[PDB]
Structure formats: C-alpha cells, structure tokens
Image 1 (tube, rainbow, N blue to C red):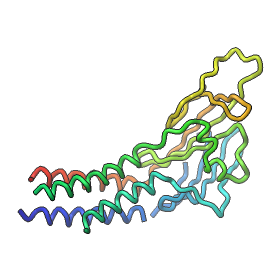
Image 2: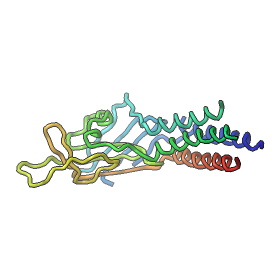
Image 3: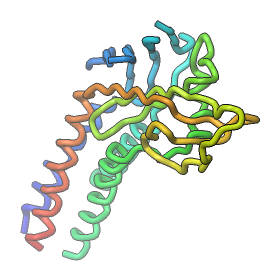
Image 4: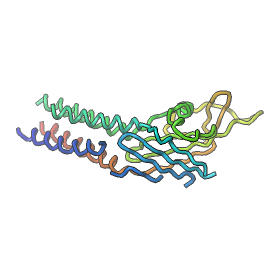
Length: 223
C-alpha cells in the first residue's frame, strides 16, 4: 500500500489552503438594526451598530474584540496540519487528524450558551463608545458560516407587578419575555433584533473540513 502517502499529501495541501483562509473580504454589512462589522481573522476590529427607535454605537477604534470560535477553529486546523507534517498506526493518525477537524467544525457550528447576566457582564458590552444604555445588550457570535449580531431590548419589571419572575437560564439566543436579575433590577427581554451575514472564507473552511474528513475516512476504510 502506497496510497497512504498520496492521501497524506492531499490532506496537507487542502488543510494548508484552509489554514490560509484564517490567516479577503473584511467589511460586512448586516431590518430594525443595521450593522457594519469589520472582521480580520479572529478579530472583530470594528462594529458600527445603528438601532432604529438611530441610536449609534461603535467600538472605540483602538480596540478589538476576539471571536473565540474562530481562534479555536484556527488552532484546531493548525494542529491537524502539525499532526500531518510530523496499519493501526495509520488509523491512529487518521483518528487524531479527524478529531482536530471535527473540533474545528464544531467550534464554528456551536456558539456559546450564555446567560443574560453573562452577556451583560461580557467585555463585549464595554467595547462600545459611547457606552450602551442600560436597556440594551449586544451579543456577537459565529453560527457556522455566519457572523451574527444580536441586540436585546430590555424592560424593567413594574412596581406591584402581577408577572411571575423566573430567571432565564443559558441560551444561544434568548427569546422575548426572558427574564433575569441585574443589580437591584429585574429585567425582561422586550425585543430581540438578530442580523447575520455569510463570511465566505468561513464557508470555504467548512467545505475544506468536510472534504478532509471524507479523505481520512476513505483511507481508514481501505485499511
């Protein structure tokens, strides 16, 4: 059997192209909310958010917000390459490479489950100039190939309220009516505005992962 080395070469070529995707388009335009986000590798370098009530919020231009899903995916790809560039032996190599690839895909596919207090306390909240008002939260994450911006409008519970208060748990996206404690207040999500844009090089990366995983499984099956 010699096809093992051919497969290892094809994997190295593909994954190096995939790695190049993480290291063209940078500016992305994201109905109630209009965003202009600049994405450089794993760094959200600028975020120009306009909410229709237009309230305008922007990052301070010094600072950048890292998207952990992209950084992690990048490191998984880099490690798949390292495993390659460094019978049952072939199968163990294939399992280790496929493990890195499936982790890279999963990190892009599965954004964090956060509580509303976690969103409010995130450094992302404090990225904005001028500061967000107390009745607005901003969340940003990657959903497979999409850059996703969520803006939550909040409403405090009124005095002598008849409403039942049950604190929301964690969620990727919270629904209107979700409630949480913040400081001396109990707040309800009144509105959820979600805008998203496809990131072409992320889609390219995902396709490369799919191809690579298929090539690994093909080789495993021949042994």
